[PDB]
Amino acid sequence: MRFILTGVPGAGKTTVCNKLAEKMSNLSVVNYGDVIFEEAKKLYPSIIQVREDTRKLPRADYRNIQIEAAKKISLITDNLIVDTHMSLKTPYGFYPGLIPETINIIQPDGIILLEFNPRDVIARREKDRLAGKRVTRDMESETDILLHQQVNRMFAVSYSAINQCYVKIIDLTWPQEYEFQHTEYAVNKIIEMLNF
Amino acid sequence: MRFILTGVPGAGKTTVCNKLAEKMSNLSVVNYGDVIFEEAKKLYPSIIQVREDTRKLPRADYRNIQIEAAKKISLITDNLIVDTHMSLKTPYGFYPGLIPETINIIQPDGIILLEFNPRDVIARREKDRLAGKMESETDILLHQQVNRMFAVSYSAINQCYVKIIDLTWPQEYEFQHTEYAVNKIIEMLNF
Amino acid sequence: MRFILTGVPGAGKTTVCNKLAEKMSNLSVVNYGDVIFEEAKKLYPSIIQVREDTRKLPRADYRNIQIEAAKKISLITDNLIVDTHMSLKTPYGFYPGLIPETINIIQPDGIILLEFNPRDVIARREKDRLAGKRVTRDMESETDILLHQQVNRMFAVSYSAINQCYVKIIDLTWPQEYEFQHTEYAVNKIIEMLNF
Ligand SMILES: Nc1nc2c(ncn2[C@@H]2O[C@H](COP(=O)(O)OP(=O)(O)OP(=O)(O)O)[C@@H](O)[C@H]2O)c(=O)[nH]1
Ligand SMILES: Nc1nc2c(ncn2[C@@H]2O[C@H](COP(=O)(O)OP(=O)(O)OP(=O)(O)O)[C@@H](O)[C@H]2O)c(=O)[nH]1
Ligand SMILES: Nc1nc2c(ncn2[C@@H]2O[C@H](COP(=O)(O)OP(=O)(O)OP(=O)(O)O)[C@@H](O)[C@H]2O)c(=O)[nH]1
Image 1 (cartoon, rainbow over the protein chains, first blue to last red):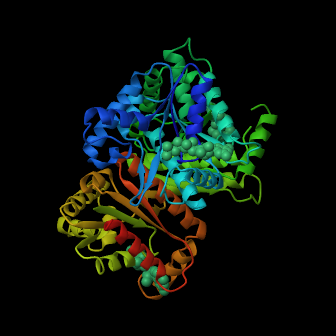
Image 2 (cartoon, protein in one colour):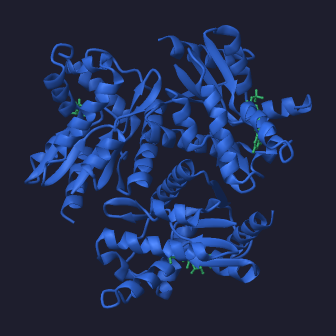
């Protein structure tokens, strides 16, 4: 099947993607941002080198790369998880991470949201910064993260009302018995979905 | 007027629909699911015999039935209540009961969401089940919030009303919720 | 830039609009519904003399006035704020204040939501009937106002899923240490947005 996998950043979503790829042969796990960066370098190289470079040029060009990234992902034939974000926080507010052409071209069966406890999100984001990852990203509060996760629900139901797809919310907000168990439980629920 | 009437399953929406059919003529109450299931046994006799088998159908085939099922309803005159569900829970997640075209074909004035206390829902579902007819109060809270988000999306898209009928208070006598819901809806139809 | 500015009624949104236009230079502030009153008088002057009189216009020609109002607003060329409502409570339930035409015609960059604590909203709506503004008393509860605000978020995020715009939630729910502090805060957050 096809599913779009989403959650707030820095909370373990990549750990879920990396571990799915390892436990399922009949599965491609692609990162929509990676492909968008890849197809950007292609179209205009002197203007594109690093990952952040994507944002600089006008939306007319950025949209047209999102179209082509989507089309390539659409060539994938086996099971597909597309790793993406329902929305990003900006000084102007939240902004959709998808565009409507992304869902028409990928024709996913549904959207998966990983919902984390905000205290975990804060802890994990702060130990990665201490290691050296996501420097000068604002320390968000518990209610910031809560607000982001609700908004994410709304975006996804909107896309469901428009495109007739499933909306699957995985609860990872309980206390872990051991480390990386949240990702373990996410990874088992998602394979159960692909195998049902 | 025409309203889409909705709520989580097993909670009393069917009792509300029946007491409308009892207490207000000049009004057609139509169960959208029954219409759809019937129309599925006409076109694909073989594949469908469980209402659950409606999505074994390829998307284009399942779309087309819900279009047709909508057209028949669409041909009705005077007041009309279309009983259905904003979403249903499946192993892949929440899925919408309406499709984009359903709303335009039927041109409803608004959507009605019957909202219950999840504790009354657990109790009611288990009562029924005991007489022949699996979710926590958190699962049910989530479901009612999703239906609320589906409703508001359908309203932004087709410019219709979104009526939330609050049935979450404790009853002073049995079937009070149902009275209250029917009176609120009849008052909406007459105004 | 262009933002649509919204909030439950009677809570402080018009105060915010007035303070913005008196403070930040060369910023246009427009109240969609005032523009709609004018457009209905120039068009139907025998039948609407009070703005409240538009109800008995056919819903089909009222819609046309919203478009004509939207078309006028769309010719403003500097920074722009459109004061309006995401939804209003009627006896048929909530109804959207915008129409799709309004947003495609105005091409707003963003939607701004002023979120208030419902006790403040009740208190403000009360002080304003004592100042002879409204003739009749508002009986919405605390939970009515939370509900109205929750529905307004969902409308905002839908318009953003559909039109690809920002959704900015300005939290005015904390308690005021002094008078008019919320309004001050929302004004300064919005100006910081426009000068970013
Ligand atoms: N100690 C510990 N760390 C965890 C646990 N679960 C997740 N993490 C850490 O939390 C961080 C998760 O961040 P990522 O998985 O890289 O998130 P991301 O979505 O890829 O970030 P973006 O690329 O910006 O979208 C990693 O450093 C994980 O090691 C846990 O149970 N215990
Ligand atoms: N996916 C899913 N569908 C359900 C569930 N429960 C009920 N349904 C749907 O509900 C329809 C049957 O009518 P019900 O929804 O049970 O009854 P009602 O209209 O809500 O009214 P009451 O019986 O008084 O509660 C079927 O077509 C099912 O698809 C559920 O737990 N999961
Ligand atoms: N005393 C006091 N009043 C306030 C404060 N903040 C807002 N208000 C009042 O709240 C009331 C509502 O203000 P607005 O919403 O800006 O004006 P409105 O035209 O009456 O209504 P809308 O435009 O629909 O929002 C006004 O009478 C304001 O003066 C405050 O901090 N202290």
